[PDB]
Structure formats: structure tokens, C-alpha cells
Amino acid sequence: HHHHMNKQELIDAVAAQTGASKAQTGETLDTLLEVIKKAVSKGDAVQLIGFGSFGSGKRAARTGTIKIPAAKTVKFTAGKAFKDAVNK
Amino acid sequence: HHHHMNKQELIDAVAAQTGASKAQTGETLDTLLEVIKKAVSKGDAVQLIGFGSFGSGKRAARTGTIKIPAAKTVKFTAGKAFKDAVNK
């Protein structure tokens, strides 16, 4: 990738456009991320139209001789508007 | 999935924990999503430690007789803490 935006740079860009303090913006982002993780961890899906949806998937146990038990996965599905934006 | 949280429910949960109005919380979320899409569309990666990173990938042209030209993809890579949370 060209550049790497970290959380502080994301907070600074967003704060500039909302007018909110960097402190409030940052707590709001941190809580948004916690709520999404909590919800998906419970087996729910979070849909953000124009961005995408977070959700979980299932992995069955699989052998490779080692053994891997079943797990859940973190799934992100980008929405049309995100994919279209990245293709321009 | 069990339940589906939409943007208004995500805003209501977050607003409750920050104290911010639902209006401010919602504009902050909308701007965060726009900034992430803009950044990835430029070829940058956004890293949110404890959640994950957004980025793009490349798809080369491929034949299947139909023809599909090269595209860019939307990539989300969940961080350790998200995966561990979903596996509990």
C-alpha cells in the first residue's frame, strides 16, 4: 500500500469535518468498534449501507498429521458503493 | 445470522455510552466511513488496532468465452483481538 493511516490520523481527518474535538471523535470511534465486535461476537451482523456489513462465519474442523478444531471467522462484505469507489 | 444491527441501532448503542447526541454520533460515523472509503480508494490502508485494517487488492484480468478485465478489491483483515473475541 502507498500510505498507512493510523487511528490518530483517521480521528484528525474526521474531527476536522464534524467540528467535534479529537477527544470526542476518538471515544466515539473506540465505542463504535467495541459495539461492532461485541455484536458480531454474539452471532449478529452489522450492516452499514454504502460501506459494508460485518458478520461471522463457520470453519469446520479440518485435518492437515495435525488437527484443527472448528472455529468462527470474522467476515466483512463490502457494499456496492465501496467497491465502486475503489474501482475508479 | 441471529440479529441484524442497522446503522440507527449502532448509533443508538454508541451514543448511549459516549453521552453524545444521536445526531452527532451519526454524523461522526458517516464521516468515518467516508474517510475510510476515500483513503482505500486512493490505495492507502487504514489500520485500527484491536479491530482490523482496510485496504485494497488487485485482481488480474481473467477469462471464463467471456472476458473480465482487471479490478481492485476491497480487503478487510481482522485483527487478533477481533478474531479472539469472535472465538469465545
Image (cartoon, coloured by chain):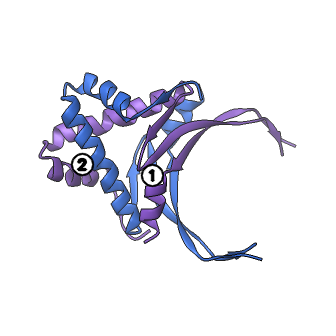
Chain colours: A blue, B purple
Q: Residue furthest right?
A: B65
What whole-number distance in Å separates the C-alpha atoms at marks 2 and 1? 15 Å
Residue B2 appears at what percent x and percent y?
40, 71
**Residue B36, numbered circle:** none
Residue A15 appears at what percent x and percent y?
26, 27
Q: Quick check: A80 left or right of A22? A: right
Label 2 marks a residue whose chain is B
Residue A61 appears at what percent x and percent y?
64, 77
**Residue A53, numbered circle:** 1
At 23% from the left and 42% from the top, the residue drawn is A27
Is B85 placed above or below B41 here? below
Q: Quick check: B80 left or right of A70? A: left
Residue A45 appears at what percent x and percent y?
41, 60
Mark 2 element type: helix
Label 1 marks a residue whose chain is A
At 18% from the left and 29% from the top, the residue drawn is A21
Q: Quick check: B6 left or right of B75? A: left
**Residue B11, numbered circle:** 2
- Which of the 4 image quadrants contains residue A44? bottom left
The quarter of the rendered structure image containing the C terminus of chain B is: bottom left
Residue B30 vs residue B44, the one in the foreground: B44
Amino acid under disc 1? Ser
Is A57 placed above or below B68 here? below
At 32% from the left and 36% from the top, the residue drawn is B30
Amino acid under disc 2? Ile
